[PDB]
Image (tube, helix red, strand yellow):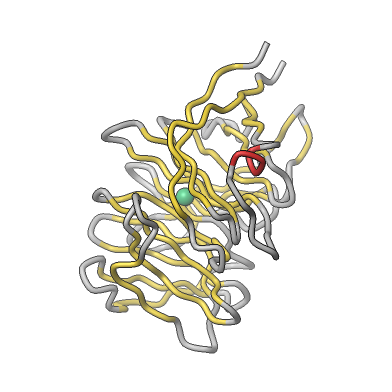
Length: 234
Ligand SMILES: [Ca+2]
């Protein structure tokens, strides 16, 4: 019953083959990426066409960054094992706040009212953007069963898209119910990426350009970001 979507590549853009993508979004014509880079973690503003960095901060050695999302004129970021997050001004990525949260923090996105965070479990949390505390909590299910390993997130036209860690699939989640209503199958997309680096890591990172309706997907150490369209299979 859950429709499956196949992809068509519209464009491929260069992606840093050393970049362990942990957070990824599109804003004001650019990509913003939270990356692990050889043991340390950075937040970068990236030119889409060239994949080159325009602006970057490197987090303190005590912290390792995970999901990031814009909120108004801020960027909000999660961490790997710190149980805390950060808020930066978007202009110069100056840190303005730290906040605590429960458990782990993997992917982060937002809709018009809330930040939405995953943590590698089936559970998604909707944060009040001022208090940065959970005001709604939902459990994600596919075929009526809990779906764990939810990672990078993106709000796309009223749905929550999520990477499922260790797979080449992206689930489309009904935000009212937590039910998976569609599955995007990206298996085989690496065969269309050109020469691959060694090592290479997993699919992870979804961004959405609301103005032009461009959907972008990438992965850890992946040599490309793909702009893709979707068609329902069968
Ligand atoms: Ca995202």
